[PDB]
Every structure is written in C-alpha cells, then in structure tokens.
Image (cartoon, rainbow over all chains, first blue to last red; front, top):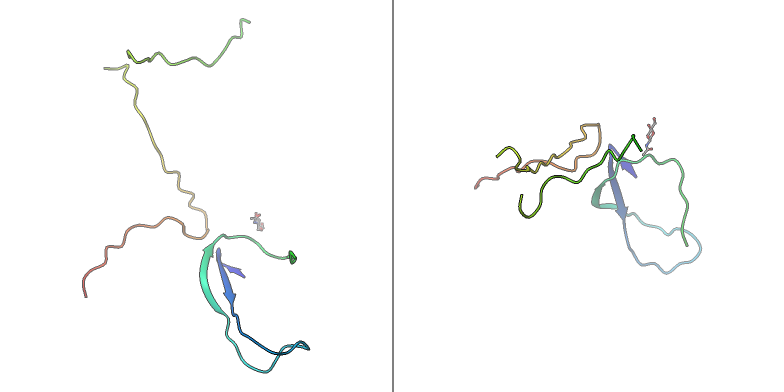
Length: 48
Length: 47
Ligand SMILES: *[C@@H]1O[C@H](CO)[C@@H](O)[C@H](O)[C@H]1NC(C)=O
C-alpha cells in the first residue's frame, strides 16, 4: 500500500504444515521499510 | 542559407577579465505535494 506518497510494505514469513486453507493463528504484518514513491494504485497483477 | 547556424562554438580554448567563463549550478526544487526526498541536517545534541 501507498499513503501520502510513502509506500508501506508489510511482510511476515511463518511456517505451517497445512495445504487446505489459512490456518488458525494471529500475525501482525510489520512495515519493514518506507518507500517515498507517491503513485496511484487501482489495479495490480501477480507476476509468476 | 541566409538563415544560418544559430549555434556557435564558444570563443574559449586552452589559451582562453570579462571573457572568463563562469560555471553555474542550480538545485531545482519541486515544491509540489509529494513525499520528502531532500531534507536538511538536524544536528543532534548530547543527552
Ligand atoms: C494520480 O491521479 C491524479 C488524478 O488527477 C493524476 O493527476 C496523477 O497524474 C496520477 N498519478 C500519476 C503518477 O500519474
């Protein structure tokens, strides 16, 4: 996400032994670094 | 033609007080509402 020109990236890497769906638990995504880009965002796609 | 080259090589050379060339630099600041990218030095003090 980007707010007030500063891109805020949040991430979290946790292990799990399950392939059905999202497991039980809580996790707060931590903003690691702030990026001053200042761009509008209304569309996006995944590059695989 | 009559309308000729508007550019001209400057009259200086490794040989070349009013004819001394001066260098100039400007830091064009874009003051639009945008994320801050250049800010001043905040000299911290001892605690
Ligand atoms: C974001 O949207 C505004 C809407 O007027 C537009 O002026 C601006 O150029 C857009 N941002 C970019 C990076 O194009």
